[PDB]
Amino acid sequence: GVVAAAEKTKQGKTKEGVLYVGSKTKEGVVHGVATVAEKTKEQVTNVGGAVVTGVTAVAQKTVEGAGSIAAATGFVKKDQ
Amino acid sequence: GVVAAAEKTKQGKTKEGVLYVGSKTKEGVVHGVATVAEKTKEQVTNVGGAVVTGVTAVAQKTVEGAGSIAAATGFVKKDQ
Amino acid sequence: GVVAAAEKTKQGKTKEGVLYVGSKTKEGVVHGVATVAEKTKEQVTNVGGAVVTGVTAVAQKTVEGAGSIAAATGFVKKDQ
């Protein structure tokens, strides 16, 4: 088996704070997620989480919830 | 099996805070999610989460809920 | 078996703080996640977590929740 399980359980005066992000840039180039190829048979890309791309990227309190991904590629059963 | 499970369960005076993002840029180029290829057979892309792309990208409290993805490509059963 | 399990359980006046990020740059180039190849058969990419890419990337309190990934590629059962 190639199974995969994950669980989480909860049985439940603070200040949040400050997050300051200042960016001064010029002539920026960014590639978040890239798959380049030549003479390929399959190209699968599954995004279950969060992909934050930019010239100024900020992520806060992003991934705390339940999600599942199940991928299976190839599988050539060429008996004779 | 290629199964995949995930669960979450809950049995339930704070200040949120401050998030300041200032960006001064010029001539920016951004690619969030890209798949380039030549002479391919399949190109699948499933987005179950969040993809935030820009010159100034901010994500807050994004992915906390239930979702599932199930992909299967190829599968050539060429018996003779 | 190629199984994989993970669990978490909880049975439950502080100041958050300060996070200052200042960036002054010029002619930046960034590649977050890249897979280059030639004459390939499969190219799978599953994102269950968080990918933060940029010229100025900040991540705070990102990955605390339940998620699962299950991938299986190849699997050539070529008996004769």
Image (tube, coloured by chain):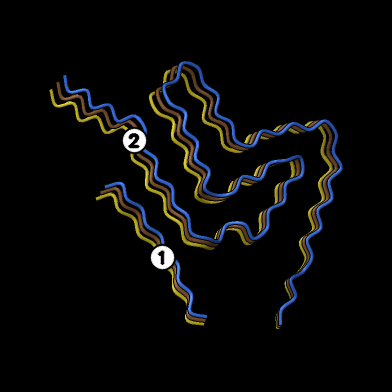
Chain colours: A brown, B blue, C yellow
Asked if residue B72 lies left or right of residue A23, the reply is left
Question: Do the numbered discs 1 and 2 sit on residues whose CB atoms are within 8 Å?
Answer: no
The numbered mark 1 sits on a residue in which chain?
Answer: A
Q: Residues within 10 Å of mark 2 (few under 14, many from 20)?
A: some
Asked if residue A51 lies left or right of residue C40, the reply is right
Name the amino acid type tagged 1: Glu
In which quarter of the view is residue B30 placed? top right
Which disc, if any, is residue A7? 1
Q: Residue at x 43, y 53 (%)?
A: A68
**Residue B62 x %, y %:** 62, 57
**Residue B79 x %, y %:** 17, 23
- Locate the C terminus of chain B and report the quarter of the image it occupies: top left
Name the amino acid type tagged 2: Thr
**Residue A44 x %, y %:** 45, 34
Secondary structure beneath label 1: loop
Q: In the rendered view, would you say C67 is above or below B10? A: above
**Residue B4 x %, y %:** 36, 53
The residue carrying mark 2 is C73
Which disc, if any, is residue C45? none
Quote the CA–CA distance across marks 1 and 2.
25 Å
Q: Residues within 10 Å of mark 1 (few under 14, many from 20)?
A: some
The numbered mark 2 sits on a residue in which chain?
Answer: C
Asked if residue C72 lies left or right of residue A19, the reply is left
Secondary structure beneath label 2: loop
In which quarter of the view is residue B54 placed? top right
